[PDB]
Image (cartoon, rainbow, N blue to C red):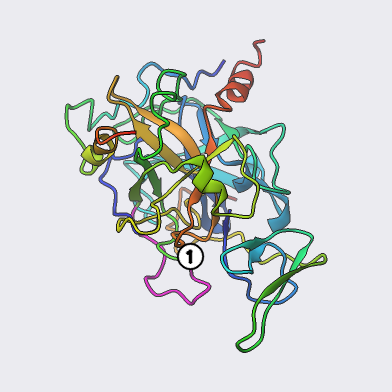
Amino acid sequence: VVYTDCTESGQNLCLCEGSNVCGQGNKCILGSDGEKNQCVTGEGTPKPQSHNDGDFEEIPEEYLQ
Amino acid sequence: IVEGQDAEVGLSPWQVMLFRKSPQELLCGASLISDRWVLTAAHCLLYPPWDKNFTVDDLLVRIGKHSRTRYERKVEKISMLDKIYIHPRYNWKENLDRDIALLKLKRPIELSDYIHPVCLPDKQTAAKLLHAGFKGRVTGWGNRRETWTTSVAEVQPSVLQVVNLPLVERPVCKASTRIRITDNMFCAGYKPGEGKRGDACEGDSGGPFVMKSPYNNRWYQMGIVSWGEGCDRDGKYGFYTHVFRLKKWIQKVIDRLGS
Amino acid sequence: TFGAGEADCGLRPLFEKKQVQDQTEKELFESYIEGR
């Protein structure tokens, strides 16, 4: 999977302490202004995802449904 | 592919696209080996944490595709899958260890200038070929950057892209990340002051990482685009499933009518 | 025994097949010949 920066505190599997994924069983504590991020231990909720794209031309009707 | 370049037509006959059947969106890449088989990276299909488990019923394969978005009526071929094999021991609750899976075409597709199967290494052209410094190849229609920065260089290519990468040495792969590294994965990228650069990215996933042979003249599928600790991140590199190290489980699922 | 291990594996109908090389392809064999 590609791992990226944690946008909310509590978040689980994200790029928390530098470019280092904060694995499961860990919580990314978003440092406030000029304070450092701290992937502390605790259960925490993973980031969102299951993406990529927005304008896919119409494919032959039945394939899809 | 982060800082690659638009691919020529036929540059990658074996580059398939895993298409979530509706929602309209590109889920990943895969390679095409038989003419009725497909090879992708597990997590594209089953990734428990992202509420990911998919069905034959939820995704379409497209082969000999260039445009990311355009439907290419005369060129590409959409195939409905039949089976979905995942690796008996695919470890998402860690490192994405042996993150491989075989798909199966609900028919044998017919090859074209746009469709060709890719090779699976042999102790000859794997042992001779997996020497760090050696440039591999990656193709994909994923992002040209990482957008959780509000991404300029609007990260989606409109055509398939390609970057060639050197193979990096084990020792240096482990020093990159905190994650445990297995045998079942090799990394590949530029040392951090090589000038040249490039990396795979979001949606490039479970896509080809091939190497051509000088000895015979084939394109070989060394690894699968497994995971990233930020695409084209500095002093960071990209992990690839090791195919050779699994060439063997693959075997046992093709036959299987066999044994 | 669906195969997957075809005999005409990774021979590009346009590139190799036609005798024609690919754009960046030298790059890869420039890797192997400066060595490791």
Chain of the residue displaying label 1: A
Q: Quadrant of the C terminus of chain B?
A: top right
The prevailing secondary structure element of the residues shown in magenta is: loop
Rendered location of residue B170, percent (x, y)? 52, 41
Q: Is B60 rendered above or below residue B202? A: above
Picture quadrant where residue B255 is located = top right
Give the residue type that dot 1 points to.
Answer: Gly
Question: On the rendered structure, is B78 left or right of C1?
Answer: left
Callout 1 crowding tier (Cα within 10 Å): few <14, some 14–19, many ≥20: few
Where residue A4 sits in the image (x, y, percent)?
57, 65
Q: Is residue B200 above or below residue A38?
A: above
> Relative to B156, does residue B172 appear above or below in the rendering?
above
Q: Which residue is mark 1?
A: A54
Give the position of the N terminus of chain B as an image quadrant. Answer: bottom left
Report if residue A61 is visible in the image. no
Q: Position of residue B159 (x, y in %)?
A: 33, 54
- Report the magenta residues as a range: B146-159
Task: Write the residue at 35% across / 51% down.
Answer: B160
